[PDB]
Amino acid sequence: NLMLALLTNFTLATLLVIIAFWLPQLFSMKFFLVAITFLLFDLEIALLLPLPWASQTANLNTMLTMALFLIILLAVSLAYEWTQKGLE
Amino acid sequence: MINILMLIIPILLAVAFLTLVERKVLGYMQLRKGPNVVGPYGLLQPIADAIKLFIKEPLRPATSSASMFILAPIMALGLALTMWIPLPMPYPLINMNLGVLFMLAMSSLAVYSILWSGWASNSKYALIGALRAVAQTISYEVTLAIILLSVLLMSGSFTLSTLITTQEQMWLILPAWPLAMMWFISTLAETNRAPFDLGPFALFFMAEYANIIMMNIFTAILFLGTSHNPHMPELYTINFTIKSLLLTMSFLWIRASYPRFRYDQLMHLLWKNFLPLTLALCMWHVSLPILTSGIP
Amino acid sequence: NPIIFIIILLTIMLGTIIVMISSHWLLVWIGFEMNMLAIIPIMMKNHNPRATEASTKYFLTQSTASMLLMMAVIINLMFSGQWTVMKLFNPMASMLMTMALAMKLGMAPFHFWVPEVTQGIPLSSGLILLTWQKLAPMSVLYQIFPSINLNLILTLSVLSILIGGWGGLNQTQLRKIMAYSSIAHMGWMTAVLPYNPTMTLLNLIIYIIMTSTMFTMFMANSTTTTLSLSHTWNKTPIMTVLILATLLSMGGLPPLSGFMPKWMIIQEMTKNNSIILPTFMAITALLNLYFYMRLTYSTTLTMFPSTNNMKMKWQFPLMKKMTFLPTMVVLSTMMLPLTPMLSV
Amino acid sequence: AERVAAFLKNVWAKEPVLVASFAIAGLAVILPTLSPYTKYSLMINXXXXXXXXXXXXXXXXXXXXXXXXXXXXXXXXXXX
Amino acid sequence: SMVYMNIMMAFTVSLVGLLMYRSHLMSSLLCLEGMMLSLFVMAALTILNSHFTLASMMPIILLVFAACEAALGLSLLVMVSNTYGTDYVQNLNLL
Amino acid sequence: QKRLGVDLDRWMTIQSAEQPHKIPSRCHAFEKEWIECAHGIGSIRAEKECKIEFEDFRECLLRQKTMKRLHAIRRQREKLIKEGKYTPP
Amino acid sequence: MWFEVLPGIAVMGVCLFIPGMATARIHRFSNGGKEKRVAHYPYQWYLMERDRRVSGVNRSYVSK
Amino acid sequence: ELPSLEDLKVQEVKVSSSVLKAAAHHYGAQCDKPNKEFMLCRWEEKDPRRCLEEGKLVNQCALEFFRQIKRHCAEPFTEYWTCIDYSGLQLFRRCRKQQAQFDECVLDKX
Amino acid sequence: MLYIVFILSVIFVMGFVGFSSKPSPIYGGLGLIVSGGVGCGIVLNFGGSFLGLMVFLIYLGGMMVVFGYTTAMATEQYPEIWLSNKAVLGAFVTGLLMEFFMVYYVLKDKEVEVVFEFNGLGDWVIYDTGDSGFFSEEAMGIAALYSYGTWLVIVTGWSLLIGVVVIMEIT
Amino acid sequence: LQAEKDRRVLQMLRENLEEEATVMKDXXXXXXXXXXXXXXXXXXXXXXXXXXXXXXXXXXXXXXXXXXX
């Protein structure tokens, strides 16, 4: 069971907190541009995720031109990051 | 189902007994003697740190905002321990339908552990440094997904059990020569304090050092293997531990030998320099199964 | 904004093409979002405190609107199954679909953002884009005009000319008058959709050309009625004749091109035995004329806006089609009687 | 040379990692078109069946036999 | 049928959440995520129970575009906090 | 579509199409009925002749007709408390 | 010297040695033949279901 | 709905446990006529109610295949069956050495 | 024990109540982790290996993590208790009672609904799927492919080029 | 594949006997010509049914992604 496996880890993690809790008795907007680019790149990663699991039944010649195409534009988005990104 | 407890209790001991390795092996690097007084070779000290911090050490919170601060270590320890479940090993506990997707997911959610700690403190003084620590982890997870896919596109599906079978004669270090170099650096971003560094505070140590062993094992699946042998589980168990231990030495090697890269120039190593390199190798790894027949 | 500004403007042009040439319901959702990410930068441009307020109001009222469309797309998976933009099938799905389209075109209960968004643009070039964006969701309505319940589409047309015919009366801001001129004309748009699909797209051809001529006449900077007042005597006097001609055509008057859509809207509606609804359309059309009537008194009357400062140097604006299109906007009554068939 | 020889050693000196970003990614497009090996990989991808093969009714057919091993149809045996 | 009855009720709660505003502006973008989350469950179940194979890719594409509006509209939120002190629906100048 | 696609095709939108693999749709037997009925212009615009075939297609995806049928059996099985009830499985 | 470092490594050759062996040796007690079947896709899932039907009653994996 | 009779088809269905059937791919070569005719019937007519008569011959021929291996050369078959179940789902990996003992005994027969 | 998905759907709505109500972006942000993580179980139970984990990777480990920045960038106001505030508790109690009243009607099978569709029981009929496919099984088992949908790949790549260029120009 | 269809007939026959036992007195349900209005092709049917009785067998057959043995 996956449900039994996950819940056992969290319940033991909660118990460790109580041990320390119960027993003893006596600005800058330049960071934002980095965070946004993380999200926009990971969505291109999300489109490029199926590649090892997808390419099994589909035609290779039709895929080859389209598979590289996403990575090329992923570099063009980084090419726009070279024309003055900032001090970061 | 008793094996889950046989993968938490010896693992919590492994994070505890790291304190010996993290300052004795690091000690001989710096020509200093580590643990010696406490035990015969200092074996009593790792368990002695637990009695010091858990029971006697009291709490003094900054504000304690109802649910938070006493919820962040649960997310820290919980996500670090659940990463052990999808691990292939000789035999995995409850094998997932897809392996590595679960591995990348629980590591991306492990970013919250350093996020909720920044929200725990009421002061503005701490949160600016806290967000900077998020930036060290969030940025390298972009490339971590790319370098993973290039190894997978060479051979095997997302399942971690198939990654052992594909390494029958030769290691994956040789075909993925520049990609193996990346996993030595990219893993150190997740609070290892080697290229960049930022009661319940003691619980974060038990979670952060747990991820260090986790990245050592995960590198020894994607790149190391040597032999499988389904008939003999004895030969695999000993040979896997030695390979993982050698990578643990290299993790403590960077911590002692090399200074911090600066936060600004961490975004010059990655993004400016690594992201054009990783994607160019990803472009190369798309063509490889098409140029020569290599499909699982 | 150098070369890439044209590329940003090109993605709005390309964005509508995705909506135009489509068979998949998720493809038009992509097409709408192509406009969402590309209008906001031109809405900002110079970065102003009024521009920040307008762009956020433009986003929140429109992004939530398109999210209601995606629900109707997913009901088309639960019911009827197929992913085709031919029919809506379910009456349950149509209620959320038509209201999502009303958030962009119907306007009768969703006008609230328009007078604030149109005023909030610092540039005259951004005024054209909002009158051009209305072409995009009209292509969707032309595809799925059957099956949708007429009882809650014609209410979006009747009430819109009422609120459009009253909402411009207490406004002196030139951008605000044109904002409620949209809602007033959008009532005529959402009336031909139940009664004969043709001439509904020709209503756009008349409207978009008429509005694009209007804002290009305001290339000589004017934002209020009093700022457009000082134009006859101090500035170019012959230019205000074309402003007069375009404003007269904006309201329903026969010797001008703007009466020619109003012909077929009533004509096709009267064929479907309905008399009580087109009567209400004609009386409310008088209220629309009143805004243009007061704005023609900046061109006809003296009004005393002389001022000490005077311009001697010749004005050189952009003016893309500010010479060819007003000639079609002033007179096309004799030119286009059989042209209803040519469009669709 | 004005751009071939001049803009090569300067690229290796100033920003040396950018050389690899154009060379490796560039050759990744060139190689799968010119090298005669890509045509073999496409055949094995189509030959490996995902679902069960369908049987057709026999009425004057060539290169079609029984399920037993016989010279019929294509049947891939490329490289061992 | 039975499972769809609860998530449609969950969709209406997220719909009202978009239409409701009290001081804070951040709730709307949080509700936009929830609306797309509720649509994701509704889309998946229809293709999973009634098999399609080809159409199972469509919610994966929907997952990508859900984040596009929840980032490019989310970027505009920060621009409000640059011009003004803090993000408020109560703080608007346009008429 | 307001503007149709010519020469080049980019669809794969409607149900019962050339699938990614050889595997077919769950409602493919009922999917073929709706396509074969509404291929002519005077069938869906009229929407009277294809009434029988669409209801069977509606029965496949929603399963509402079978749900109400199984509801009556499960209720009557629960109704037979302290009474004669069939048991074999 | 290494004689101080090696006990720190040898203790890691026991604690990390557990999860590998404990997952493998449990298949002797749970299953008949020291093997656990992997699901992946319905093809292998159906074979697991029919094996229990082929005279096994409670057992999922059983020979003959 | 009109369902089939309670007696149905095939007396004592299936030989034994799984993986045993997956171990031998010789089931494709020997006895193919009943398997292909059932396949040809079912794709033409999707209903199981009509082509169940051909399916009766499939299960009967299935027993005929396994009985021939149990009579002659049983020792290499049992050893190959123990090899495939000891491992996970390799099927042919790390069992090719024991596969050499198989087929060689079967080669004496046709 | 009988139901698997139906219990998770109640917790899904339970997390969503803090959105119609206004408990500040801190506690309101916490709702998407609760509703999202449980929301994966609703997707996973009927199938979908890849698509079920995409919520964890993007919606949970990407979307809301960026939203973690913006809460600190704009409107932080030091996190407060969501019980002392007026009308917030009133919106929360009315939000749950709209769904929890329907939970009581689930018993004795049939429940009253605003929609025309009936709910009934549907426990074994909740999945409503046979075995069918075996090797390379499930419609979501091969969920995404670059083939056939070639046009979709171009526009998604185009839209993600816009985002990087535009957001850089605003600031 | 035959083993799938052999089970589907046997599961339906047990359901037919239960319908005849439960519906006798008040309800006018005859159970004829099935749920389908066309009644010519006949789909999976027992994908949603699979016998309502005995939950221990129903939970293992329906859920495959959960646990996954």
Image: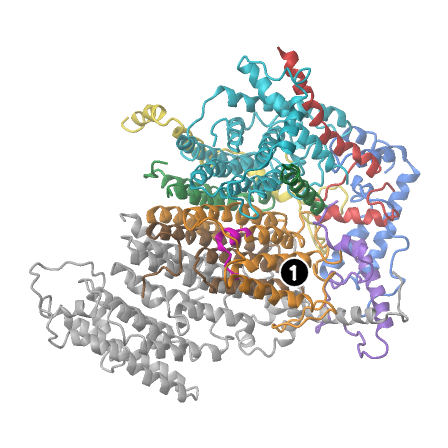
Chain colours: A green, B cyan, D yellow, E brown, G red, H blue, I orange, J purple
Which chain is indicated by disc 1?
E
Of all residues, the one furthest to the right in this rendering is H71
What residue do we see at 26% from left, 79% from top? Answer: C289
Three-letter amino acid code at disc 1?
A: Ser
Left or right placement of residue G21 versus residue C26 in this view: right
Segment colored magenta: I20-30
Q: Position of residue C8 (x, y in %)?
A: 33, 52
Give percent across and percent down for residue J38: 70, 73
Q: Is residue A12 visible?
A: yes
Can you give x and y, in whole percent of width and height, for residue B10 in the image?
Answer: 70, 30
Along the line of sight, which residue is nearer the eye, C214 or F79? F79
**Residue marked by disc 1:** E50
The residue positioned 78% from the left and 56% from the top of the image is: J58
Residue F49 vs residue H1, the one in the foreground = H1
Q: Secondary structure at mark 1?
A: loop
Q: Quadrant of residue H54?
A: bottom right
The answer to whether B48 appears left or right of B150 in the picture is right
